[PDB]
Amino acid sequence: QSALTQPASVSGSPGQTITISCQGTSSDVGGFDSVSWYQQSPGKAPKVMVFDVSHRPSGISNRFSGSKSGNTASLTISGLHIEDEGDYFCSSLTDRSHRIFGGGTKVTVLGQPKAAPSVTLFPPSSEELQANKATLVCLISDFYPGAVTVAWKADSSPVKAGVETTTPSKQSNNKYAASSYLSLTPEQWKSHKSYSCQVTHEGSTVEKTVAPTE
Amino acid sequence: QEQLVESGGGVVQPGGSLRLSCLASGFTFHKYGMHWVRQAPGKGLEWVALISDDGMRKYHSDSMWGRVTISRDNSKNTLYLQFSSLKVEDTAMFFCAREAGGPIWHDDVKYYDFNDGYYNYHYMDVWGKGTTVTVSSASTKGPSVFPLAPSSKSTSGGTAALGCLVKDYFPEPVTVSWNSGALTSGVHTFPAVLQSSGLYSLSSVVTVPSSSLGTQTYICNVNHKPSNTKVDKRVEPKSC
Amino acid sequence: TTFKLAACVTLACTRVKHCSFNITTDVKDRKQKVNATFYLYRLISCQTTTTEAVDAATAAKVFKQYANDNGIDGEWTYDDATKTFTVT
Ligand SMILES: *[C@@H]1O[C@H](CO)[C@@H](O[C@@H]2O[C@H](CO)[C@@H](O[C@@H]3O[C@H](CO[C@H]4O[C@H](CO[C@H]5O[C@H](CO)[C@@H](O)[C@H](O)[C@@H]5O)[C@@H](O)[C@H](O[C@H]5O[C@H](CO)[C@@H](O)[C@H](O)[C@@H]5O)[C@@H]4O)[C@@H](O)[C@H](O[C@H]4O[C@H](CO)[C@@H](O)[C@H](O)[C@@H]4O[C@@H]4O[C@H](CO)[C@@H](O[C@@H]5O[C@H](CO[C@]6(C(=O)O)C[C@H](O)[C@@H](NC(C)=O)[C@H]([C@H](O)[C@H](O)CO)O6)[C@H](O)[C@H](O)[C@H]5O)[C@H](O)[C@H]4NC(C)=O)[C@@H]3O)[C@H](O)[C@H]2NC(C)=O)[C@H](O)[C@H]1NC(C)=O
Ligand SMILES: *[C@@H]1O[C@H](CO)[C@@H](O[C@@H]2O[C@H](CO)[C@@H](O[C@@H]3O[C@H](CO[C@H]4O[C@H](CO[C@H]5O[C@H](CO)[C@@H](O)[C@H](O)[C@@H]5O)[C@@H](O)[C@H](O[C@H]5O[C@H](CO)[C@@H](O)[C@H](O)[C@@H]5O)[C@@H]4O)[C@@H](O)[C@H](O[C@H]4O[C@H](CO)[C@@H](O)[C@H](O)[C@@H]4O)[C@@H]3O)[C@H](O)[C@H]2NC(C)=O)[C@H](O)[C@H]1NC(C)=O
Image (tube, rainbow over the protein chains, first blue to last red):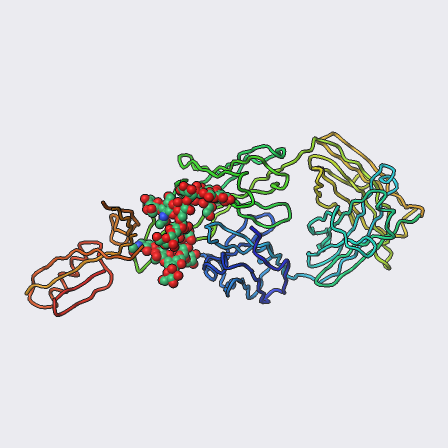
């Protein structure tokens, strides 16, 4: 019941070749030649690109091709067009006659210079504190391609609970922005010496910090 | 003109029930098996259920088994999905998809299944628009708007970032503007994030020149029609 | 001179025996799976006929112009000893 494993994000220039892998088990991907790939364009419904591992439905460009080996399958797009941009999901028949999808891969067709995110970390407002609440806001903006992962830290320790993050969305200048929130009690906020927001973009990390001070 | 159209989506409370339906056209409905697939906000596709052409064989995913029942009425080209004991976690977009199928070719002879039925080709070749299902315990409620005092954005380049924190409201949506829409440049309002309370929260930020602070006023206008709430919050520089 | 033709189809089984097989359903090119029982191992069912001719050519004809008048095809084996053709 755990999805097939795919890379969260990949990207390439127009005309570039790229590949997406789909890791499974002998009860699905390694058990049948029934792996299919679906593309999901923003706004539109999913659409088959490849089925039975390496077959294409009528209408699909020969650019798309798939292969399989053991428990992993792969989709290759040799020569990205701009319309290849979107989310890609592998899918496999199971030995119980169910279907299982992969976690999905965001595919970006690089159409502008890559940009690292600028990160601004807002401490709890005085008004919210008086209302007996505390929210840390991590503003992530002006980055490209539009895919990031966020991680919070109280002092040196990582923080899992009370976290909520938005999916990156396009700004009016065509770069991407996203937001992350950390909820705390007014006590926790003043218990630690500092809190930190760590953003990872294209493998490179950017971090900001805030401390309870007036 | 193969087409699928889902409907019946809406808000339900956890533990409750709801039935979705998918109207098919452009093809012989009763010859094809049919799927339901969900997609939680910002998450991936997840297979839910499959039902055979004649509706005699059903399959449900292990993660939703006990909370879903798939069915169909071939006499009116409709696929159904009956929910029960719904969980907050089940909130998602639900898609209606057709299972590709037909005969299996060995030489030039087409082989069909029992009762001349199609074999499955093991991929989905037609999809619907999808309909949204929201599982929530929340009553309609207006937001609390807090200010995010300006903070240095561009270390150099002389830019700061300020905004409004609009938290704990239901249902969507909330509209946000700055100085009554007079300020547009550098404005960005993020999608809503859902807490475990079942209430929504969002932020609206704007990038502005550090030099203008103290001589330029910044007010956000939050409006939540569901509760008839309108709020204007002045965002100003903080002391220490 | 009279020769033989064995027309055979494939079967799968398991007193009571359960079996299934594929059959022509109106048209030569179309087949369909079916269940059948009586009152797991592979099997083959065969019906035999004998059209009379003079040589192993005309026979080959009539035996092909019979698989014509029916939805028959597949592989053809010939044992000269018994002058037996075998479609499957
Ligand atoms: C012709 O003829 C034929 C013959 O006869 C037929 O067919 C048939 O049919 C029948 C019925 O109809 C069936 O039966 C079944 O069986 C089963 C078993 O089987 C299996 O296995 C086997 C094996 O064998 C052996 O041997 C041989 C030799 O001899 C060999 O070969 C092998 O190898 C081995 O060794 C086999 O045989 C089979 O096979 C088949 O199939 C496959 C696939 O799968 C294929 O491949 C092949 O080819 C074939 O086809 C199989 O595999 C069993 O199991 C079953 O049982 C069940 O049921 C019943 C009734 O029916 C009852 O009674 C019982 O009890 C059971 O029940 C169950 O229970 C459980 C508990 O325990 C449960 O679980 C649960 O589940 C849940 C869920 O639920 C559900 C959902 O999802 O929702 C429900 C639904 O309904 C369902 N569906 C169905 C369709 O099923 C589902 C499913 O199940 C799933 O999904 C799957 O995946 O589910 C949850 O999950 C929970 O958790 C749990 O717990 C369940 O539910 C229940 N179920 C029910 C249903 O109820 C039965 O017995 C048979 O099989 C057949 N056979 C054959 C050969 O095929 C036909 O029909 C005729 N045709 C005409 C048309 O005529
Ligand atoms: C009457 O006609 C029918 C139809 O022609 C015929 O049924 C076949 O029977 C043979 C022999 O038993 C079966 O061969 C076995 O196949 C096993 C695996 O089957 C799975 O994979 C199949 C291949 O799928 C690939 O290709 C197809 C396109 O052809 C494509 O759709 C797939 O996506 C994939 O690319 C697949 O067709 C088949 O599908 C059936 O089951 C699925 C559920 O899983 C269902 O959704 C379908 O609708 C359909 O019912 C299935 O998914 C294979 O494991 C097995 O191997 C055994 O034998 C070897 C030795 O040969 C051993 O080494 C091994 O250990 C195994 O024991 C075997 O090869 C074939 O699958 C049947 N075909 C169909 C359509 O079901 C009957 O035999 C005919 N009857 C007679 C008596 O003549």
